[PDB]
Length: 405
Length: 146
Image (cartoon, rainbow over all chains, first blue to last red; front, side, top):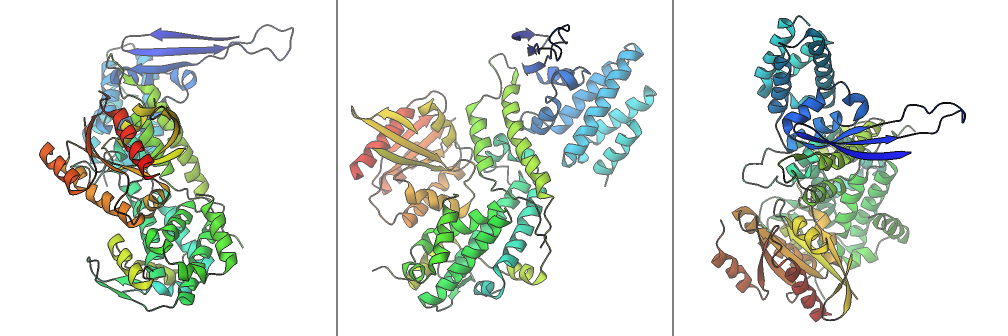
């Protein structure tokens, strides 16, 4: 019925899971059992053997995409490419039949890799590319298609109170526009807890750029809300260097309502990144205090605000998730499971859990491409000229605006 | 009978490493008494400005975690101490400084423990020494406030 048994090989460990399904005709012979030989652990070289095996496509369907997406966690791109060239050059002396079929798998694996993660192929792999290119001509072997594509990748002061001037849904569209294109630019392998977790380490300032870009925009929005509601513009690094607009509580309320509606419009656009930027910013400590202003706020705005806090035309069918839940999940996943087993074998089960999460943001990326958002250059230049307050600046202004009693 | 704990620090410090070993919400026995605790991690979400602010509002006790290797991660500890005081405007609040070994001197670690009215404890990544002590230490300081 359902049978599971382990295996062991040169430098790897497998697990076969063959389930016998009942035939469609109850009196017919048993149909061939549906089986899946899945790699569980092994050396880096053994992983490349499994990678270049023609059987893997059907036996371990999701080994290839999982290795490719996660390899930067335990290796580098030129090494992985290098080992694939090692194997192929080793098979040169072999009988031509075994050479062709593997070359074929190698062609198929690299093309998938190229389509899935082009930003992997920099100038770092120039030698490995030559290695593969020499091979294909030497053995006489979409080869030409792959080489063409690989070579083309290896060888190439605004007023924050002016938010009231724009319609709220118009603002959400612009914010969604910016968040969405950053989410499309997101390289999901950079979200891995073994890379994002070490972003602060003494040599990783240029590591994980696409993820950081997402965070910087989340912080610019949360800054914009905080700075707007306080009616203050940051003119220096210091806690005192900032000009404040004098505003009565009823006037501040109008800024609260505006942003609450901006949040709500982001929710209808399914841009949760900015919903969470606006909401957490409204719940932020320098703006949470402002009771007078919060007391002057229309009650329907407060209900929408509650409804949003409890979560935490053709306006495009898309989504921008709050990355952070994902980053949390990946960071905790990196710390919960070990990189390597006691024998020094790479724990490939961890990567499988990792890739499953990386898969979900891949489908969200494809969903995100359904967005129909039109650029607004007036809102865009307003945002670009916006100078947000530091946490120290915002706390000082809040006290000067609504003093403690 | 629920004590909300927050673990604060930089990435790569291993708050998440310290979190998982204490448990693997949890029902525990403090002083012969059944208590539940929430450890809410800022894991992966450390660079998000307004997010941690929301955590610190509901959180009743804090763990300030830095690594004993990096100077940079230890330097960021006063920022986290500042952020907590901004959100919770009170000096007398449950707090614990945590060094995590996996370069910065021990005498310089004890200095910041002395500057504030809160104890300092060092912990190891997988040796699991003082891993239970750290939470149990803070929970009592939370219960003290209760």
